[PDB]
Image (spheres, coloured by chain):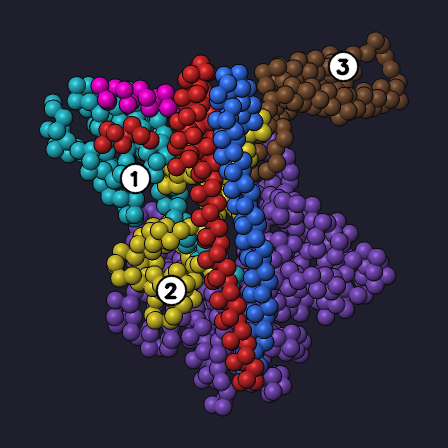
Chain colours: A yellow, B purple, C blue, D cyan, E brown, F red
């Protein structure tokens, strides 16, 4: 079942509370849509009314924080079209080789902040290098990650 | 539900989680003053992170060490807090799996079984011996275990999923002994890091910065001649530390216990002794399948040095492979949670009605 | 070979069940589009019949009332009306 | 200022664009298009060039007026009043600071890597 | 929440002028009567706190909380994490603080008065 | 075992052809649904507009004639172009 870290919850909390200083603990579904497109996704009116139907049987027009968080978690959870996968690899690779060197991974790790060890990084490289060429192509990245 | 008395770092997860939801330090606090100083003293109990944060008003011990449950009440406190805070549940909804060190005296084994059954509501339950399920994480039924960095340092040869009780022995060094030697060599170097804060900083240093020399005499002469092999570290106070021979001298104590002054054969030769104790037919499988575990193994270079050293001890006919799970400081928890996931394992448990007549005898028996 | 054959047997039985699911889903698609075209045909014939009534104003009034009551729902069209009013502001001023 | 002159000046900050259109009503309405297409990995919804109107992509373009902002994609239109667009830009500024949002594609992808490898072994 | 908190304050405000002890006696007494009347007083106050006071404040605040709908204040919480996140928990923990503070005053005023009352005899 | 291997690899390949074909047919049905549902939009929105149109019988008649003509067979922006 989808989950995200307590620090991710804290960040989402700051997002919610800045989204309106009015301290209501509930905010407009329209602003939820503005949030999603600020993340980079502009869902269509069918998805707008679908999510509204989730949030607001009563029709306040408002998520509470737990709805905001749970719908965020779900929309975070699913798989993307290839464009976003390419974006991911292009950020992972700034050697511009189409290869995730161990350097590329290690910098991405230092950027995100999780301190996972060098053998663990090299092992997820090794399994992610689905063709075993020495590191992971964007092809090999696709091949593992689409699974 | 999965429960670990991990004596360097204790841990908990629901069964078949991918990781222990909760990880927590092997301590419970008592108020250090005998009176309640202020309303913070709502309990006399401060399990885990509570002690770590609040040390100064609290009484401080690792409740267990080495081979046994030591101090049953304080362990029961730890387990109670594990269920209610850390697992955040009343457990009795689901079976619970628990850890014990190898060759735990049967008296303790039943005493624990009783304590868990009577003190905690439970459907069915089992305690497992850290080596056996640690080997399950390897995937072998047939393997010798090493573990260091979460307990005293065991050797355990295992055939088809069970030990040779004939061949269980400790090396009486734990995570503290590594910190002790490292504090010695730091004080020689002049850092003299020994205060409880310095002690924690040095435990961080030893956890991340240790490495095991491939051939210690050569690596030590290399680093002492070529200080390019000794590497810099930033202290929380902005000092820079340089760490060099210390990086591998500290793990070398496992190979030369006399380095920490211990009159023992090294981990390699005591492993070789353990193997020799068993059937040569098993011995070949143990040389084929060695598993090493615990925070001390997590380091770089340990498994390569160990592979070389066992090859030096092992007969030239033997194939040698150290198996080094990247997670191996959790091996037991991984194996236990995986095994407990299986609904076919559900028949293996012991539950209330059989627990009455059978349970004292039947758990003692199923615990092997 | 033996493991390869057995794996292929399990794959092909899975793929058969996937085929049957896909065939029944496209069957649902085909009957759905058949119903949609039957709806379109009923619209067309309703328009031709009210065009047949058109010759009497009372008959056209009753036809417009009946087709209003049958077809209309506020739908998006209230929103379309508002946003069309706003876009009509934009259009008129930029036209000017 | 004068309209083609300000086009050629080629300023691109949405704040300054809004200020310009508010200030110079006689210069009329302006349409704008993004300094890279959405296909880019460094694409930004709020960095845009303001151009002579024919040049824009027919199928995806933005429009502003001192009366109103409006956007169209693939014959789908939304109409906006400029203060909504401005405050949504302010939101995007602050939302962009948000550590996960600043990183989310990394966050989820590398997490999936971790999950897939450990679940597999 | 104002109505709830003011209500529990009123409950404390009679509570704070109760006593945990019978700091008053008409004349001399024999020992067993002291033991009886004090143990009775203790039992009476313990039933009053555990049944009467806690239940009373709980149902009263709930009744006020009842019709606060979705938002931070949601009685109908479903996640411990979000409850800890909420203002609601922090408010409740303030209720905990206030009612502990008040019973602390009651304890002090009972003990001090009782001891002074003995003091006026023994001094 | 070789003969069985060839049989099973052939039959799986044949079923993968089946699924590819059924995908293509689903894409044709998707086209049909898309066009029909957009026509349902067009007709219902035109009906709503003729209802909104001036129910003076002459005006209603002319609107009906307009719909009859166009069915028997976004604008302003295009004119601005």
Classed neighbour count for the residue bearing mark 2: other residues with Cα under 10 Å, few (<14), some (14–19), many (≥20): many
Give the farthest residue toward the top: E26
Name the residue nearer the viewer: D96 or B129. D96
Q: Secondary structure at mark 3?
A: loop
Query: To which chain does the residue with label 3 belong?
Result: E
Judge whether residue E118 can be spotted in this image: no
Residue D113, compared with residue C81, is above or below; it is: below
**Residue C94 inside the magenta-drawn segment:** yes
Classed neighbour count for the residue bearing mark 1: other residues with Cα under 10 Å, few (<14), some (14–19), many (≥20): few
Name the residue nearer the viewer: B197 or B314. B314
Q: Secondary structure at mark 1?
A: loop
Q: Is residue D54 left or right of residue B56?
A: left
* Same chain letter for marks 2 and 1: no
**Magenta segment:** C79-96
Name the residue nearer the viewer: B84 or B109. B84
Q: Which residue is mark 3?
A: E23
State the predominant SS element of the stretch in magenta.
helix
Query: To which chain does the residue with label 1 belong?
Result: D
Spatial CA distance of label 2 from label 1 is 34 Å
* Same chain letter for marks 3 and 1: no
Residue D121, compared with residue C62, is above or below; it is: below
Q: Is residue F1 left or right of residue D82?
A: right
Q: Which residue is mark 1?
A: D59
At 81% from the left edge and 61% from the top edge, which residue is drawn? Answer: B359
Name the residue nearer the viewer: E71 or B103. E71
At 54% from the left edge and 73% from the top edge, which residue is drawn? Answer: F11
Tag of residue A140: 2
* Same chain letter for marks 2 and 3: no
Tag of residue B35: none
Locate the C terminus of chain E and report the quarter of the image it occupies: top right
Query: To which chain does the residue with label 2 belong?
Result: A
């Amino acid at each position: 079942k989808p989950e995200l870290t307590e620090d991710q919850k804290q960040e989402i909390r700051e997002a919610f509370d800045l989204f309106d200083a009015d301290g209501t603990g509930t905010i407009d579904i329209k602003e939820l849509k503005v949030a999603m497109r600020a993340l980079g996704f502009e869902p269509k009116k069918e998805e707008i009314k679908k999510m509204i139907s989730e949030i607001d049987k009563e029709g306040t027009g408002k998520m509470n924080f737990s709805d905001f968080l749970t719908v965020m978690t779900q929309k975070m959870s699913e798989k993307d079209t290839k464009e976003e996968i390419l974006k991911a690899f292009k950020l992972f690779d700034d050697d511009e080789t189409g290869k995730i060197s161990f350097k590329n991974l290690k910098r991405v790790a230092k950027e995100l902040g999780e301190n996972l060890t060098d053998e663990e990084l090299q092992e997820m490289i090794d399994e992610a290098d689905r063709d075993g060429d020495g590191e992971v192509n964007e092809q090999e990245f696709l091949r593992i990650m689409k699974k | 539900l999965v429960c670990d008395n991990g004596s360097g770092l204790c841990k908990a997860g629901f069964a078949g989680d991918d990781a222990p939801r909760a990880v927590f330090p092997s301590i419970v606090g008592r108020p250090r003053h005998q009176g309640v100083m202020v309303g913070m003293g709502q309990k006399d109990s401060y399990v885990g992170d509570e002690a770590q944060s609040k040390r100064g008003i609290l009484t401080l011990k690792y409740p267990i060490e080495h081979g046994i449950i030591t101090n049953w009440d304080d362990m029961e406190k730890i387990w109670h807090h594990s269920f209610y805070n850390e697992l955040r549940v009343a457990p009795e909804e689901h079976p619970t799996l628990l850890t014990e060190a190898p060759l735990n005296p049967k008296a303790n084994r039943e005493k624990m079984t009783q304590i868990m059954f009577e003190t905690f509501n439970v459907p069915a339950m089992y305690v497992a011996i850290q080596a056996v399920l640690s080997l399950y994480a390897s995937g072998r039924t047939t393997g010798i275990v090493l573990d260091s960095g979460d307990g005293v340092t065991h050797n355990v040869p295992i055939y088809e999923g069970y030990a040779l009780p004939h061949a269980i022995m400790r090396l009486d060094l734990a995570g503290r002994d590594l910190t002790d030697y490292l504090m010695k060599i730091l004080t020689e170097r002049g850092y003299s890091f020994v205060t409880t804060a310095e002690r924690e900083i040095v435990r961080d240093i030893k956890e991340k910065l240790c490495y095991v020399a491939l051939d210690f005499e050569n690596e030590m002469a290399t680093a002492a001649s070529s200080s390019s092999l000794e590497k810099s570290y930033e202290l929380p106070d902005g000092q820079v530390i340089t760490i060099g021979n210390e990086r591998f001298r500290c793990p070398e104590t496992l190979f030369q216990p006399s380095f920490i002054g211990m009159e023992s054969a090294g981990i390699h030769e005591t492993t070789y002794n353990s193997i020799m104790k068993c059937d040569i037919d098993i011995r070949k499988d143990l040389y084929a399948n060695n598993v090493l575990s615990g925070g001390t193994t997590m380091y770089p270079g340990i498994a390569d040095r160990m592979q070389k050293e066992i090859t030096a001890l092992a007969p030239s006919t033997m194939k040698i492979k150290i198996i080094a799970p990247p997670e191996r400081k959790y091996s037991v928890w991984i194996g236990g949670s995986i095994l407990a996931s299986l609904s076919t394992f559900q028949q293996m448990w012991i539950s209330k009605q059989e627990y009455d007549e059978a349970g004292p005898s039947i758990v003692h028996r199923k615990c092997f | 070979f033996h493991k390869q054959n057995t794996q292929l047997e399990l794959n092909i039985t899975e793929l058969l069940q996937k085929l049957r699911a896909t065939d029944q889903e496209m069957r649902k698609e085909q009957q759905k589009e058949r119903d949609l075209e039957a709806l379109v045909r009923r619209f067309k014939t309703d328009l031709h019949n009210c065009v047949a009534y058109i010759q009497e104003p009372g008959l056209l009034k009753e036809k417009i009332r009946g087709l209003f009551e049958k077809y209309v729902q506020r739908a998006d069209m209230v929103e379309i009306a508002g946003l069309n009013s706003d876009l009509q502001q934009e259009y008129a001023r930029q036209r000017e | 200022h004068d309209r083609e002159e300000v086009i050629k000046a080629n300023i691109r900050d949405p704040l300054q664009i809004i200020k310009i259109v508010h200030e110079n009503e006689h210069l009329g309405f302006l349409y704008m298009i993004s300094a890279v297409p959405k296909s880019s990995i460094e694409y930004d919804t709020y960095n845009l060039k303001v151009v002579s109107y024919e040049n824009i992509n027919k199928n995806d373009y933005y429009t502003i007026s001192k009366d109103a902002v409006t956007h169209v994609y693939n014959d789908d239109i939304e109409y906006i009043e400029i203060e909504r667009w401005e405050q949504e830009y302010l939101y995007h500024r602050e939302l962009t600071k948000i550590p996960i949002f600043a990183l989310f594609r990394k966050w989820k992808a590398f997490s999936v890597w971790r999950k897939n490898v450990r679940s597999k072994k | 929440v104002i109505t709830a908190l003011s209500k529990v304050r009123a409950e404390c405000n009679k509570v704070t002028s109760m006593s945990l002890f019978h700091s008053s006696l008409s004349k001399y007494s024999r020992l067993e009567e002291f033991e009886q009347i004090q143990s009775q007083t203790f039992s009476q106050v313990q039933m009053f706190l555990k049944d009467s006071w806690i239940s009373t404040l709980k149902v009263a605040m709930r009744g006020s909380l009842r019709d606060m709908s979705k938002g931070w204040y949601n009685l109908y919480e479903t996640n411990w994490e979000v409850y800890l996140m909420s203002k609601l928990r922090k408010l409740m923990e303030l209720i905990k603080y206030m009612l502990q503070d008040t019973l602390r005053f009651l304890v002090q005023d009972s003990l001090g008065s009782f001891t002074q009352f003995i003091g006026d005899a023994c001094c």
